[PDB]
Length: 259
Ligand SMILES: [Mg+2]
Image 1 (cartoon, rainbow, N blue to C red):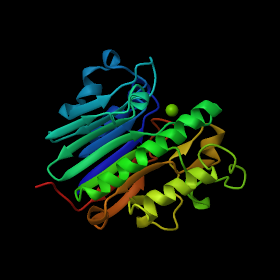
Image 2: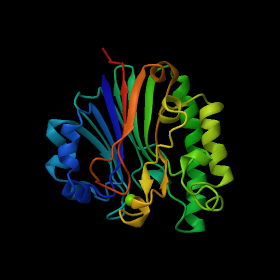
Image 3: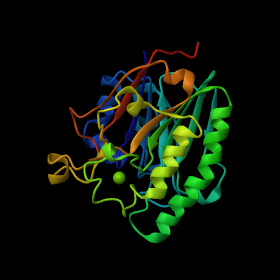
């Protein structure tokens, strides 16, 4: 099967100290989309550019130690898009797209809003700029997986403390509505929720201490998929046998090849 892994690595240099490099190979992944490199190109070792000889494409931020995304693939993409073409967001290294024939896979790091109202506003402006891109992408008629950290939990099932987080970034009414539109208006499939309707599937906890031990989790990482490819998804899991990051890798297996 085609195995695609989405992982917010909370700093690729940190994740590599915790075994993430070995996992890229051991996992059997064909494509690994990572978010939050916290590294510029000058900081990336050869094994962070082309892990295990994979092809790698990345978009780093202008600020040091910040953001950045990458897509690693066993096969060579025939086309690569670095950034969205919106300067404000592209300066932060948040979007890479790799094409393999009629398959496209994206690594997306959606802005977080919990730090300050200014950043919640950036987050909302990102949502408004990205929605028409999602619409256009859906209308391409190609097979597309948008992997990444969307920084929004959709429904009560998607986080442990839904009662106490309705005024906090990640579970605001406007944010949840926006994800709902991406699914129900645009017709993207939330692959995890479609595969396993009743299984929470948290992918983030604020630390590896109490927050993790007590499973105070949120499902904020997704694979959003086009219709025909969604029908080819056979299984998924949140990988928790090792801990590389404050997020867990989201792994989906598709009965699909680009040739
Ligand atoms: Mg982080």
